[PDB]
Image 1: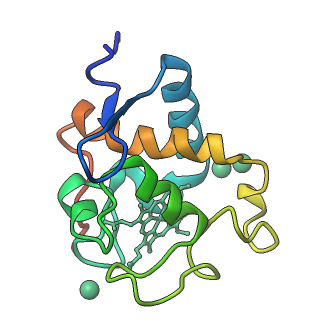
Image 2: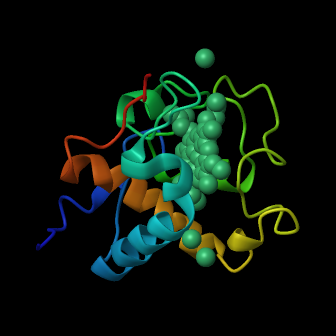
Length: 135
Ligand code: HEC
Ligand SMILES: [Ca+2]
Ligand SMILES: [Ca+2]
Ligand SMILES: [Ca+2]
């Protein structure tokens, strides 16, 4: 399926600037997502908290908002609770703590940029991306 440049263009930070991933960067981000993120976020969902999925509306409500690439990169370095108060660096996988997340130890900052871009392109691609799982 061909993905155009507009689809691969997503917010870079909060003030209106955007970034466009290459096809290669998209591919790499998708691959990392499948290998490392789908154990807890299949289809962009979250099941152990409400409204803290990878869907855009949920990301937008985080503190600071996570619906832009740089905020996602920051989260994957130094994860926090949704209100930003609590340090999740020993709770959520991240590249700061390869000692406890060895599956993260070979990803560079640029790899994390690619999965962050992937995460924000994915909802454009799939109406079912994101959401809270309820039982
Ligand atoms: C289970 C072992 C997880 C793995 C692997 C990954 N994530 Fe995760 N993530 C998980 C939980 C339980 C939560 C909720 C935290 C909370 O505040 O209760 C999250 C949350 C995120 C978020 C924030 C979503 C928001 O709407 O603010 C992001 C951006 C996120 N996780 C990303 C992410 C990525 C890209 C991962 C692969 C590198 C990844 N997570 C793995 C649990 C788990
Ligand atoms: Ca894996
Ligand atoms: Ca809650
Ligand atoms: Ca792996």
